[PDB]
Image 1 (cartoon, one colour):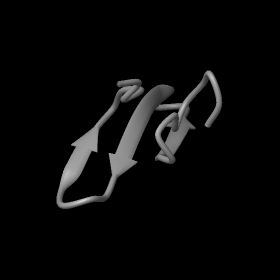
Image 2 (cartoon, helix red, strand yellow; image 1 turned 180 degrees about the vertical axis):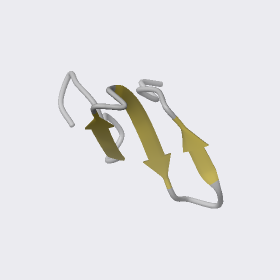
Image 3 (cartoon, rainbow, N blue to C red; image 1 turned 120 degrees about the vertical axis):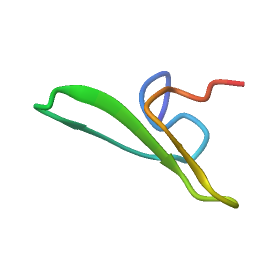
Length: 37
């Protein structure tokens, strides 16, 4: 994670679709963004 992708212990990946996506699985969360706060 770090000051980069998957900040809050997140499963993020950057495929050449070349976009940054975020898969956070608490209940049901799916968005392509750093969740910072």
